[PDB]
Length: 216
Ligand SMILES: [Cl-]
Ligand SMILES: [Cl-]
Ligand SMILES: [Cl-]
Picture 1 (cartoon, helix red, strand yellow):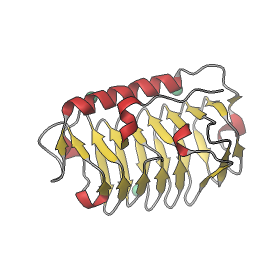
Picture 2 (cartoon, helix red, strand yellow):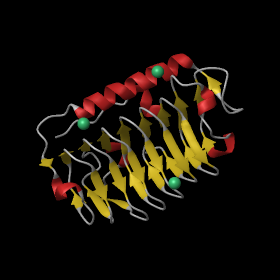
Picture 3 (cartoon, protein in one colour):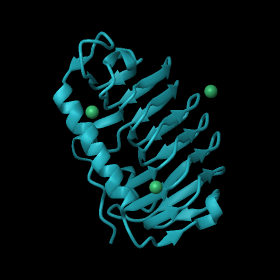
């Protein structure tokens, strides 16, 4: 059975980036948010958008920010460790499933790899037990089209789903994502898309009136 990806201190964040968090008011984020090593001024959220704590590396940022460089440095390091962990998993159960487009599929537990960009243009289901683990390795971008829902079935839990992407992630408007995202570049959400999962970007996270909830 596939091991979880240990997020370390990054597990405590709904959104964690390295070059900031952009936002088209109003979003609704549940969980802590942070960015490092960029200045906290690059976190463009307000306090009424975040249920939790906004962490900054310095004295800049939203009014409600907490300055804690050492925690952010550990979280971002742990985020990098998790990204490398997840990208380093060997012996995939699936390789280039659906030839890079996977609309309509039901995904069972395991390690999946794509040597291209992955597209999700219609609804999909992730199906498994409450202890099963999915790891999706994407060597290109990860795209999901407008209004696409990812449905969880059989007891599958968002906290046991990990998406590792070497390129940028784009979630289209009204879409609904499930699982943790470890992006090597950005994670870009569009108008009123939602995610039950974490947004861990090694560049920036950009939002447009999104709902972001940390997995329970
Ligand atoms: Cl850092
Ligand atoms: Cl990769
Ligand atoms: Cl846009």
